[PDB]
Image (cartoon, coloured by chain):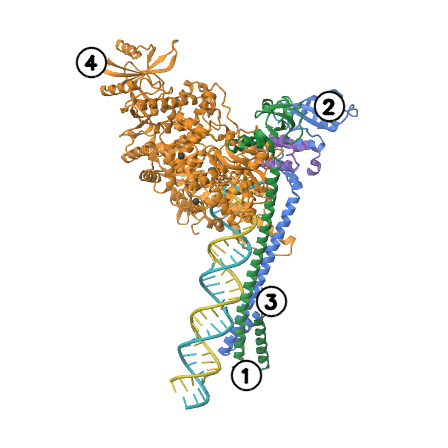
Chain colours: A blue, B purple, C orange, D green, E cyan, F yellow
RNA sequence: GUGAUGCUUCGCGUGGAGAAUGACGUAGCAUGCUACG
RNA sequence: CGUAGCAUGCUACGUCAUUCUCCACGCGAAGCA
């Protein structure tokens, strides 16, 4: 505690104590200095205690406002924060199937239903282009989620069956994209 | 060795699905809950990862719900 | 073989019965059978070895053995004369097995022989013992009984856990097939008694003197009397048979017209609710010679012992009556001229019909108290609601209060990625690590609350051994003699949290604070006095719990109405606070585990047992499978502290309110009302203490069964032998309470069966020598008691035993024990599962809690919990606590940095430097304070 | 404090003492004027302590009055809400059938569990699977509780309207079970 | 829409007992000095 | 040696200003069972 009106009184009295004791003065002066110094000490203690209480109250209020602000920030941005966290964790996992399906989704090739796990498994996968088709499909086998599937039918944008032979680099402009390939797990 | 990462990731994934209002579909939410709880009660890493792929298929199926390209820079 | 074949022909006795011996010639056969014996030497219901009978099995006309035996008994001439005279009196009775008295020249003298003809292989004693001492390891009499009477097929036991009520509910059906046989036995018993009464024969009826066809034999201890003054004694018979009458559902035939299983069910009047005369007719039909008064309505009972006695019979008989007849009895009152429908009574399965004493018709106004009572009552809600046929459950559905069914899901927990990243950076969660994440927040779908409520199907009507229960209740109340109870005033009540739910329908206008502020102490005392004279049926709201666990289960708790909770507090809080303020007792509720409390509790339970072993158990689905009789007994034990403040009627009406509110009340589970079959409503004012009473009752019952089912001749200790004899006398031969023997048995249990009870958790330090000799209960006895008195099979994965007491109990309140050098002496410290603490750190139930900087006291509490792991000999468990300390330091640093960035201040708050040093947490387990 | 005249008396005494000291005190009586100052200080401090105590007690009493008024004002709110709910339920139950069954009662009391069974005009059946559907509420009309119910509506767990033709053995996997069937008591 | 009870940590407030420093009033023991008798 | 008045040292009680240990309760937050 410094820069208080009673702090200067304390400094002056305590500095004068050394002079009084070392000045060879009478003990009446000693009692006078004791009285003045102790009175200033008590007054400065009162002022310092009140100032400490004010600082403590300021600290508490500041902490509470910080907590409310942080809680509001944390709750408001829950959605985007959770999504970013999810994809950071997925990237850290570095699994073959997860990376495969995530890359296909980034390219626009997404499923229309939960990717089944059993052998008796019907999966419908959308395909928005011929390039992704040829990259992720060839012949009558469809590689997806680090697994092999056997195609059954492709039904184009407007529902209409398409034979596999009808999908090719020359034939791509004719077809009505996007396509929907339904396949069975290998 | 990628067995506590999968369970935490499944928790975060089901939280994200819940944020995307998937409980509005009783069947889809039931399947999501089944996958999540099975992954949590899993000892085999391969079973957990296949269930994780199935669970992530729910998020990836809804094309417009999330913007994958921005999320995965 | 001429002598043997001649003996075989003589046993036929004119009745061509195609006999084939069971032993070599005339040599007497030996079998190991259950006998309910009591004489000057031994007393008990145990398996003895009989070697004084020759069995000749009768075979069908096609050489197929049938269940008909000719048991030939060899006698002294005196008893041969005595039994012949009694039989000649009892010959005309159709419930008496045919006897043939003859004399056979064995070697050189005419030895007397008494042939009981066409007897079943097993007796009623064998069935009762097999079901009351069930051991999955060796249950061959039970299997043979089931197969022999076509209850099931011999391959039915190839299942795993075929005997488990939870894993294999179909076992109930298999047991129900026996019911009719048991019923016939009961009927025949009555006939036999009548014959005795008409023949002037005085004797004791025992289960082992009746076969599974209902026929009776023996007559060895029957004595002549005036022809019309016969006095059958049936206490042991009926009391030992009682637990089997509900397991086998014997009285199911009573639900059919003409009491015939072929004919259809009786079509009772739908508006009928008073079956008092039907209950009396059932009692006279079956328990005619049970010589203690039965009150169909327990409002007329003399004391709590009489109440339990008659409630047992009411439990048995209520299974015959339609479920729609039980519940609030709603009358039409007129208030201010408008017609209300208000519950003016209640039909209890156990207590019969109760009618409110203050039913004010033509009321002029409703005050706050009356308005609250009417709002609580399910009369208006059920009467004005739609009809519900919820097929998702078997519990009786009453009404749908809303036009849409509510499907409430459970959402997953929030992942604290900061703490998890920190942990993995500090070498956690690696493959092969002993510490791995096992506690999560499991999500649930819409059918979550209803699916968990459906677990009340494990609650079954359980008739108890009443003579045994009336002694067990006294011994259990001996455990609650160091406590002070009694009603208190509304101003003396302490409410821990007033920001909790007030129940239904009161949760749609405020919390409990609203109704504790709106209700004046005058109003609260008026409501209490009302509940002392009237029954208030309340609605219980089933609420899902959002908690972290290792088991994929959605716990549901009961939010009980504010009206019920207020009065229950005012009625029980004095006793509950006395219980929680007591140290060193059996019930250790209110005892802290910090500052040496764990060590004190363990040293107290150890006491001075001679050969100390530890054992412990958990009740599977404790609240869902608790019998109604045991819950009523627990409530009566708690209410017995009201001998100076409440009269008999006041205590009974408080019991009736407790039953109507937290035993079989109306349950609101998803906007619809259902009827709870029974069991505790976890969420009432006394859940933790009723559970403790129930646990102590089960333990005392296990000890009683262990001591009475022990061959008395094999007890080398005369004190224990006389104690067993007196125990049998006090159960099945004394009607009043023998306080001296109750104190003797309590002292015996305390000396050899020291207990430490906290709700459904228990730790027993027991004398292993006595347990091995069968003098005190072992874990097998506890399983046997639970099977027939709780309708739950207890597996060994739910129980544990510890030979070395320096290891402490294996688990208690989810805490493990470690004996660690703390200063100059070794102390027992509790430590949790490291996975539990790590899951608490990593997974939370609030988005704001995933930011650790705001929640630092949370991690301080977690570190306080995790401290005793530093003393563990495993370095991973020890590192768990240091992980929390380091993360607390990091959180404080981050908080200081954020406060410096957002503001232009300096926290310089290292009074918090004590939160990342071990002394703050080490001081929490030292006995200083 | 300042309002109290004791503070004024102390101020006058202190001003007099300060003026006497500045002008030059005699010798030993300046100690006596300081003594008067000290007496004033003690008495004024004692008065001010009671001043603060009474002020804070009055503040506590005002807070108590505010809380009591709020409690009495919320009691009225909850009373009115309970009365409104009770009146709504009164005007929500059919009086004809209820009166008939209550009059058929031998003494006046009836089981509560039969009131909806015999008087409810609308039934709600929750079907978990298709086998239960075919067993319980197949067709447009069905018999339950010794009464005939005409199916009014069917919805799924998502509250989507379901046509009775949609419910079929092959189409069951496509429905969001359980189904809620709302039916009306036919001809009362 | 989130129950009953137990224990524990933290923050805040009021209250009681007690410790320390200091101002200061009354009374009393007691040292020194002026005046009256 | 008594009385009045004035001054110095030591001690008891009473009331205040400040701090802190322990506690009884109240309120808020949290953790575990
Ligand atoms: N949040 C909780 C948890 C438990 N209990 C009480 O503790 C008893 C038993 O707890 P627990 O054994 O954990 O529940 P169970 O129903 O027995 O489940 P489990 O089969 O695992 O033993 C219950 O009867 C319940 O009333 C409670 O009141 N509140
Ligand atoms: P822990 O192993 O959770 O339970 C030990 C014991 C059993 C139970 O009755 C009681 N308990 C536990 C948890 C809870 O939330 N409430 C409660 O009463 O303590
Ligand atoms: Mg349990
Ligand atoms: Mg437990
Ligand atoms: Zn009775
Ligand atoms: Zn009482």
* Marks 4 and 3 in Cβ contact (< 8 Å): no
Asked whether C136 or C836 is in front, the reply is C136
Residue bearing the label numbered 2: A155
Give left or right: position of E20 versus C607: right
Chain letter, disc 1 residue: D
Labels 4 and 3 share a subunit: no
In the rendered image, the quadrant that contains the N terminus of chain C is: top left
Labels 1 and 2 share a subunit: no
Q: Nearer the viewer, mark 3 or mark 1?
A: 1
* Gap in angstroms between the C-alphas marked 3 and 1: 35 Å
Chain letter, disc 2 residue: A
The dot on residue C168 is none
Residue bearing the label numbered 3: A4
Residue bearing the label numbered 1: D26
Q: Nearer the viewer, mark 4 or mark 1?
A: 4
Secondary structure state at the residue bearing disc 1: loop
* Marks 2 and 3 in Cβ contact (< 8 Å): no
Secondary structure state at the residue bearing disc 4: loop
Q: Quadrant of residue C67?
A: top left
**Is ligand 2 within 8 Å of the beta carbon of the residue shown at mark 3?**
no
Chain letter, disc 3 residue: A
- Label 1, residues with CA under 10 Å away: few <14, some 14-19, many ≥20: few
* Gap in angstroms between the C-alphas marked 4 and 1: 148 Å
Residue bearing the label numbered 4: C108
Give left or right: position of C345 versus A82: left
């Amino acid at each position: 505690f410094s820069s208080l009106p009673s702090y200067a009184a304390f400094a002056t009295a305590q500095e004068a104590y050394e002079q009084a004791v070392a000045n060879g003065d009478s003990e009446v002066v000693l009692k006078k200095l004791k009285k003045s110094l102790n009175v200033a000490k008590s007054e400065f203690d009162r002022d310092a205690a009140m100032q400490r209480k004010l600082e403590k109250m300021a600290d508490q209020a500041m902490t509470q406002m910080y907590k409310q602000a942080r809680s509001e920030d944390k709750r408001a941005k829950v959605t985007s924060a959770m999504q970013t966290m999810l994809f950071t964790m997925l990237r850290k996992l570095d699994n073959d199937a997860l990376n495969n399906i995530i890359n296909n989704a980034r390219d626009g090739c997404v499923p229309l239903n939960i990717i089944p796990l059993t052998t008796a498994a019907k999966l419908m996968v959308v395909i928005p282009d011929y390039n992704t088709y040829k990259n992720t499909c060839d012949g009558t086998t469809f590689t997806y989620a680090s697994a092999l599937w056997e195609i059954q039918q492709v039904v184009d944008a407007d529902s209409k069956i398409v034979q596999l032979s009808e999908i090719s680099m020359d034939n791509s402009p004719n077809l009505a994209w996007p396509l929907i390939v339904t396949a069975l797990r290998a | 060795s990628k067995m506590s990462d999968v369970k935490c990731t499944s928790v975060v994934l089901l939280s994200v699905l819940q944020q995307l209002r998937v409980e509005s579909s009783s069947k889809l939410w039931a399947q999501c809950v089944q996958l999540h709880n099975d992954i949590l009660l899993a000892k085999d890493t391969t079973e957990a990862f296949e269930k994780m792929v199935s669970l992530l298929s729910v998020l990836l199926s809804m094309q417009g719900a999330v913007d994958i390209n921005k999320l995965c820079e | 073989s001429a002598d043997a074949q001649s003996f075989l022909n003589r046993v036929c006795g004119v009745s061509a019965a195609r006999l084939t011996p069971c032993g070599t010639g005339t040599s007497t056969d030996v079998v190991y059978r259950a006998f309910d014996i009591y004489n000057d030497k031994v007393a008990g219901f145990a398996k003895f070895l009989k070697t004084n009978c020759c069995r000749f099995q009768e075979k069908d006309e096609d050489d197929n053995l049938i269940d008909s035996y000719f048991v030939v008994k060899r006698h002294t001439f005196s008893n041969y004369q005595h039994e012949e005279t009694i039989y000649n009196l009892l010959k005309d009775c159709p419930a008496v097995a045919k006897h043939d008295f003859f004399k056979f020249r064995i070697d050189g003298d005419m030895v007397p022989h008494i042939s009981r003809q066409r007897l079943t292989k097993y007796t009623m004693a064998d069935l009762v013992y097999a079901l009351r001492h069930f051991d999955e390891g060796n249950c061959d009499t039970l299997k043979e009984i089931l197969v022999t009477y076509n209850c099931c097929d011999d391959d039915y036991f190839n299942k795993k856990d075929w005997y488990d009520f939870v894993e294999n509910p179909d076992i109930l059906r298999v047991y129900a097939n026996l019911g009719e046989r048991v019923r016939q036995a009961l009927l025949k018993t009555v006939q036999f008694c009548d014959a005795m009464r008409n023949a002037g024969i005085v004797g004791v009826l025992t289960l082992d003197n009746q076969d599974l066809n209902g026929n009776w034999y023996d007559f060895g201890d029957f004595i002549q009397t005036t022809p019309g003054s016969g006095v059958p004694v049936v206490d042991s018979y009926y009391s030992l048979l009682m637990p089997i009458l509900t397991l086998t559902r014997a009285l199911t035939a009573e639900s059919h017209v003409d009491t015939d299983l072929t004919k259809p069910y009786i079509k009772w009047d739908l508006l009928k609710y008073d079956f008092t005369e039907e209950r009396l007719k059932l009692f006279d039909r079956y328990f005619k010679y049970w010589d203690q008064t039965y009150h169909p309505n327990c409002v007329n009972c003399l004391d709590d012992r009489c109440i339990l006695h008659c409630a047992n019979f009411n439990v048995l008989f209520s299974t015959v009556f339609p479920p729609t007849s039980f519940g609030p009895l709603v009358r039409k009152i007129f208030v201010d001229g408008v017609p209300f429908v208000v519950s003016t009574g209640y039909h209890f399965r156990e207590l019969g019909v109760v009618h409110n004493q203050d039913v004010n018709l033509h009321s002029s106004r409703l005050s706050f108290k009356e308005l609250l009572v009417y709002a609580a009552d399910p009369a208006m809600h059920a009467a004005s609601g739609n009809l519900l046929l919820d097929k998702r459950t078997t519990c009786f559905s009453v009404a749908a209060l809303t036009n849409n069914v509510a499907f409430q899901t459970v959402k997953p927990g929030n992942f604290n990625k900061d703490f998890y990243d920190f942990a993995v950076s500090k070498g956690f969660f690696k493959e092969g690590s002993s510490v791995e994440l096992k506690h999560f927040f499991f999500a649930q779908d819409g059918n979550a609350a209803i699916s968990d409520y459906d677990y009340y199907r494990y609650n079954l009507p359980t008739m108890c051994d009443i003579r045994q229960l009336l002694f067990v209740v006294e011994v259990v109340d001996k455990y609650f003699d160091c406590y002070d109870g009694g009603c208190i005033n509304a101003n003396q009540v302490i409410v821990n949290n007033l920001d909790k739910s007030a129940g239904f329908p009161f949760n749609k206008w405020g919390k409990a604070r609203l109704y504790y502020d709106s209700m004046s102490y005058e109003d609260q005392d008026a409501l209490f006095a009302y509940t002392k004279r009237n029954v208030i049926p309340t609605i219980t709201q089933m609420n899902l719990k959002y908690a972290i666990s290792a088991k994929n289960r959605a716990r549901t708790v009961a939010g009980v109405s504010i009206c019920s909770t207020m009065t229950n507090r005012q009625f029980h809080q004095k006793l509950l606070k006395s219980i929680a303020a007591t140290r060193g007792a059996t019930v250790v509720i209110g005892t802290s585990k910090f500052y040496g409390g764990w060590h004190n509790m363990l040293k107290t339970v150890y006491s001075d047992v001679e050969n100390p072993h530890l054992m412990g158990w958990d009740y599977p689905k404790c609240d869902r499978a608790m019998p109604n009789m045991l819950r009523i007994m627990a409530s009566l034990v708690l209410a017995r502290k009201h001998t100076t403040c409440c009269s008999l009627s006041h205590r009974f009406y408080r019991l009736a309110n407790e039953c109507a509110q937290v035993l079989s009340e109306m349950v609101m589970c998803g906007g619809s009302l259902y009827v709870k079959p029974g069991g505790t409503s976890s969420g009432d004012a006394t859940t933790a203490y009723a559970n403790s009473v129930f646990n102590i009752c089960q333990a005392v019952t296990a000890n009683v069964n262990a001591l009475l089912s022990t061959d008395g001749n094999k007890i080398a200790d005369k004190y224990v032998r006389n104690l067993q004899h007196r125990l049998y006398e006090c159960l099945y031969r004394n009607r009043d309470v023998d306080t001296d023997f109750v104190n003797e048995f309590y002292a015996y249990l305390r000396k050899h069966f020291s207990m430490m009870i906290l709700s459904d958790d228990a730790v027993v330090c027991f004398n292993s020598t006595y347990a091995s000799q069968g003098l005190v209960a072992s874990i097998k006895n506890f399983k046997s008691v639970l099977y027939y008195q709780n309708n739950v099979f207890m597996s060994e994965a739910k129980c544990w035993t510890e030979t070395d007491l320096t290891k402490g109990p294996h688990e208690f309140c989810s805490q493990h024990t470690m004996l660690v050098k703390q200063g100059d002496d070794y102390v027992y410290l509790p430590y949790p599962d490291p996975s539990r603490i790590l899951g608490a750190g990593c997974f939370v139930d609030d988005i704001v809690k995933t930011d650790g900087t705001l929640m630092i006291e949370r991690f301080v509490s977690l570190a306080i919990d995790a401290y005793p792991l530093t003393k563990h000999p495993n370095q991973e468990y020890a590192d768990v606590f240091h992980l929390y300390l380091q993360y607390i330091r990091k959180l404080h640093d981050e908080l200081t940095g954020h406060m410096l960035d957002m503001y232009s201040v300096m926290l310089t708050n290292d009074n918090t430097s004590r939160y990342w040093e071990p002394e703050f947490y080490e001081a929490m387990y030292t006995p200083h304070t």
